[PDB]
Structures are given as structure tokens and as C-alpha cells.
Length: 361
Ligand SMILES: *[C@@H]1O[C@H](CO)[C@@H](O)[C@H](O)[C@H]1NC(C)=O
Image (cartoon, rainbow, N blue to C red; front, side, top):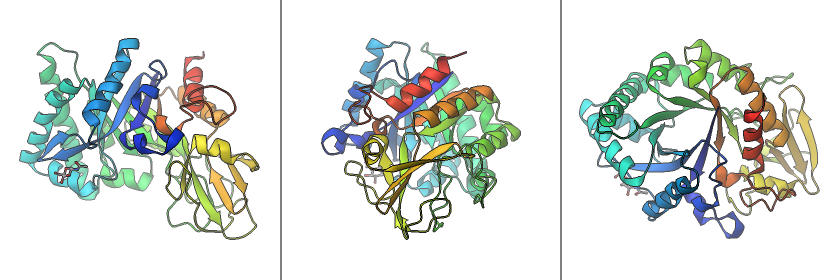
């Protein structure tokens, strides 16, 4: 099985124990670590942070200890606007320029591949994404002739049915990609004025937003669209999402006034790192959504949907049962990478739980 793990370049800047550099990553934890994100500038791949050449080197130094570890560099993300990808992918010349720039940059920096994280392709982009993936793979095939093991090509793909339908030709891009990481953790609509879970494995009993807004639906639908199971990797979050409650109510359908207050370390309303949730749980009441198979917790006016060791184990057992290629974790810097917040003196408790289940049989 593959265990694909993202590291984000901006996590370095978090205050105190929040700060995460790539030497905090256990070299044997994941099969693949993806550094996120690269820029695109003058239609060529490029660095983003001031110190990315340094941190790329710190990541790639992990392979001294684990020579089998593979690294990838992800291009795009939400700070890069989808419109920027669109402009590059939609024209033969800019697409070629970009694609030609990729292998030398990856080689120089010690990466084993490229991950595409276009968030997200529209209706007008679908055919261009197909061309970009096909043509980038073709360039990786040519570059391999100069003697070094062929670069890997992956993509991070929406897990929302409407987004999938609008933007991706899954049957075609699956042929050329080495794996597809399914973003099975953005299932609570931005529009909703109630609490809910963003990463449920199955639908809830009572007005799920769709029958579609759950990991099981997403996996099934990618298989049905022609993604072979051995190309599909299911995403599992190490962060949770938070809400400010509008009333004393906390169970299904509880109204909310907006996102939850930011975490001390991650400083972003509506999201909390797992290590922050560990701490939040002190004094919190914990609940599970029985049919969705994922937990939430509440205290004061704050309500948090999250994933725990149990839930991520459960998701790993599911994905093996569906004979998928493995798991993807977003993100190492949001798991308890220091080991010191979650009461177990164990680094990477979520990601490690996933690993441990992938090895079972
Ligand atoms: C990213 O590339 C754009 C396109 O050139 C550029 O304007 C911007 O300075 C670059 N962003 C960063 C964070 O380097």
C-alpha cells in the first residue's frame, strides 16, 4: 500500500511548538512525502517560500536514512489561483513551456515526481487538464531515457461529485497518473448554517447535504468513472473543522453563527490541527456520528468535527477492503508531529495509526 503524506512549506512559520520543518518528519512513516506548494512563474515551475531550496534539501536528506522514501513536489494549491492554471493549460505553448521546465527543476532539487494540485478545474478546463496530464507524463517518459528512474506523476482531485463531473476526465487522466489522491475531507458545504462533518465515511441518517457528500460515495464514483482501484488513494485529514454554535444545541443540525475561533498555533478560523484538538478535548464532550463513523467534540460555544485514531484506522481498513492503492494524509504538520499534545508520547499518532493498519492482513 502507499502512504502519501503532505508537508506544507508555510508550517515553518507557526509560533512555538507549531513550527514544523521537514527534519521533524519520520523518514520511515510514509512511502511518499509531497512538499507543498511550488509556484509557476514565467510559465515554469518555481519555488514559493524564500527558503524553499533549503527546505527541499532538508526533506530530500530524509532519504539518507530511508533510501526507499519517494518525494514529490506539488504545484498549485489555493494561494496560486485556479485561473493561473487555466491560462497555462489552455494554450499549447504555455503548456509546453511548463512541462519542459518540470524535470530539470525536480532533478536539481532531488524530487522523484510532480503532484498536480489544481484547485479546481472548471468545465472549460476539463479537456486541458487531460492534455496537461498526458503531455506531462509523455515528457517524464522521455526524460527517463537519460538513465534515472522515471519521475512520478500524481494529482490531488476533488472528492465532490459535482466538482468531479465539472472538471475531470477521470477515465483518461487515470491512465497517465501514477496515483490519484482523493480529497475526501471537504464534505461540509461553506453555505450550511448548521454543524456537520467534513470527512464522513458514509452518509448520515438525517438530511445528509447529499447521499454524495461522503468518502464512500466518492470512492465508488471514481471507480465507476474508470479510475482503477490501484491508482486511487483515499485522503484522510489530520486537521479538524470548527464552528461557533448559535445555541446550546450540539447534535445533528445544531445551528452555527460561523466558523470556530482560531487555534493558537494554526491561527485560521474554522480549522484546527490535531495537536490543537488533542488539547481542546480537555474539558470537552465527545460524540461520534454512528453511521458516518467519525467523531465530534464540543465545549463552550465551540464545536469541532475531527478524525481520531479510531476513525483513521477505520478509513484505512475501508480503503484496503476496496483494494485501493493506499492512503493520503493532509498534512504531517497538522498531526501531533512532536508527540507531546495527545497524551501518548508518540509522534504522528494519526499517520502512524494509518500506517499500522495498512501493514496488517
Ligand atoms: C509566483 O509567481 C508569480 C507569477 O510570476 C509571481 O508574481 C509571484 O511573485 C510568485 N509568488 C511567490 C510567492 O514567489
